[PDB]
Amino acid sequence: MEVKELERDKNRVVLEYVFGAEEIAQAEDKAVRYLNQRVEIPGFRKGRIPKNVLKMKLGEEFQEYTLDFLMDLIPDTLKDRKLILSPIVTERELKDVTARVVVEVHEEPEVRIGDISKIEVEKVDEEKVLEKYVERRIEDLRESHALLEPKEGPAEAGDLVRVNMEVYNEEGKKLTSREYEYVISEDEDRPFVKDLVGKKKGDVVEIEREYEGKKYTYKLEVEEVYKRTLPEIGDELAKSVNNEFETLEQLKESLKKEGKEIYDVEMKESMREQLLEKLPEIVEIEISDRTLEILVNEAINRLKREGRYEQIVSSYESEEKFREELKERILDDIKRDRVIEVLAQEKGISVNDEELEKEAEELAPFWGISPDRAKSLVKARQDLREELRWAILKRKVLDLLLQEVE
């Protein structure tokens, strides 16, 4: 029983596991036990069929069983290695006084963080970002705070029409009701608003439009008309907060960096995702080309098992060329991941149950159940607590390398 690393191929070792005569026996009569309870031939009672006789029925078939119950001893050796792919047995052999097994062991590959500074992101102008958002938010704010009193006439340009909408099926059965508030302007027209210019309180319209499949009939009663002269950008707009605000500066000069709380995230996040995506360029790996082919073939044959293959491969250039093209994709994650993988522990980072929670709490809206139910889903399902672990871990690691483009 000697493990001889026959060969290494970067991050892929091949090992010769050899088993002397003593063990060859130990797995042989340990296969006659198992086989016997599978086998059934006249006379010989339940489990009691002598070894040779069994090896009589199987013969060359038997060799295999001896081998498997020697082959199970292999797993008890690569306990320490964290590998990309489950050990693959290239050849398994047995002769007179020897049972040889050749196992290929595809361990997770090594990487090398290059020049983390030599990486271009794209930081947008906080000032011009901020003023642009604010300008428009004053646009927004004076709208929803316009000076409105019910016009007694009709409805021309620039006036709010409160309309009560009812939706009926083609078969005349009301589906639901609603109320809306459309604002009109100069010579402008859009479905179910156009036909509602120069109408009064009480007056009705019945737009019959066809959607998706069936004919739908929309009853539109004008609930009220109101006059729409909005506050001009000043301190009279500071009525948005009833106490507090008294100057427009208090509105602007605030929002100018009130919505800085949004640039603080959307940007950080974008920056993060840029670096994440860009990461492979500075990262050298040593993956074996066999390890490439195998994960590549595994990716393709599963793309095959699903259906979304001939959708994608048969919509590019050829067949062999997508395989080449996918290979350049798989590698770059093998890259991105293992960079975080190391950098995580090698820069003192691990993801705890606590932050795992917060994460699933804001993820809950995205699954449709209670925020408290998500944690239960995390506690139950493993695949899911591991998926989140790695997801935060990434947030963190990328969150340092980026805060380090020096």
Image: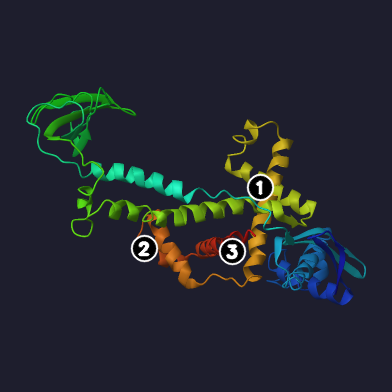
> Residue 307 falls in which quadrant of the image?
top right
Q: Counting residues from the N terminus, which is met first, the one under dot 2 or under dot 3?
A: 2
Q: Amino acid at mark 2?
A: Pro
Up-down: is 130 above or below 109?
above
Q: Which of the pair 40/142 is nearer the observer? A: 142
For the N terminus, which image quadrant? bottom right
Nearer to us: label 2 or label 3: 3
Instruction: Describe the element under mark 3 as helix, strand or loop.
Output: helix
Determine crowd level at label 2: few under 14, some 14-19, many 20+ residues with C-alpha closer than 10 A. some
Residue at left offset 75%, top offset 57%: 285
Judging from the image, the colouring scheme is rainbow
Q: Which residue is mark 3?
A: 400
Q: Counting residues from the N terminus, which is met first, the one under dot 1 or under dot 2?
A: 1
Looking at the rendered structure, which numbered label has been put on residue 299?
1
Nearer to us: label 1 or label 2: 2
Give the percent coordinates (x, y) of residue 6: 88, 64
Give the percent coordinates (x, y) of residue 136: 34, 42
Up-down: is 103 above or below 182?
below
| Residue 263 appears left or right of 3 | left
Residue at left offset 55%, top offset 55%: 272
